[PDB]
Image (cartoon, rainbow, N blue to C red; front, side):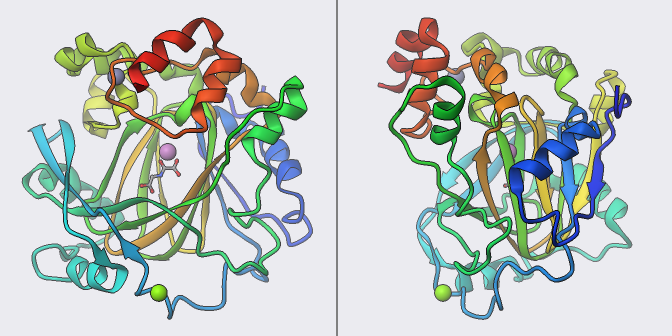
Length: 331
Ligand SMILES: O=C(O)CNC(=O)C(=O)O
Ligand SMILES: [Mg+2]
Ligand code: NI
Ligand SMILES: [Zn+2]
């Protein structure tokens, strides 16, 4: 069995290997990459996402979110307070202000220590989940707006045509902005490209050990667990590496830099934080190996997680027993 320790693998495709997205994902899996839950892909040196980032300041962040923490430094929840709209140029200036800028630090490890010691004491502002793309339309390889759609994959594998669309989303971050512990909707894959700016640190639990993370989460967040059997779908819970190590949870960590892709694999729980002003683009995708994970994915029926239009069909076809309950939570 390849990659039995479930380490995060890093890939360097050539330009020829970069031409066929599906084939390369299947290659990475042949080497055991999925066992980690996360892989890094460094594009060939001939590739670029677009020519420059000089013309992005007029993008609007309609609903910036202030991420307010509650709990203790290693075990906390965050909620999202809506703020007034601002442009990417206004957000960048805010990110670089003395109130929000990255502190002086020695290296990534020192910054990670500072994040876990100090995150809860501040409320950074995140531009999340903005529908759109920064890939040039003439970028032909690994263009996140031109991938095969999940609805087309379900049709090819299972024969059923379904409604829905699959589009990318932008993320504008600053120091301490945080993505809470989660798997993707319907335990899909994700691909994430860091277009510009400062790094993003990731934590991940191997898919084969996901239930260990869920059990610890129910212990650490006992009221949230009573409220919802799939409360990590709310995307609010943070647990530090130190706490994970104290509780014997298997995980890995890696830092993504500008110009790099990360792939998350079905049922790979992940969390992380931004080092400073940055912009990432992400989208969900599927392969034939996802289908069996999609059939088994948990679902939030409490009302909180409130998702996309296109998840309806996935629940309806893959999880018909759960459909009625899950839809009552959506309405
Ligand atoms: O960058 C983000 O805020 C978080 N990314 C992801 O959850 C992803 O691409 O799977
Ligand atoms: Mg612009
Ligand atoms: Ni994700
Ligand atoms: Zn819920």
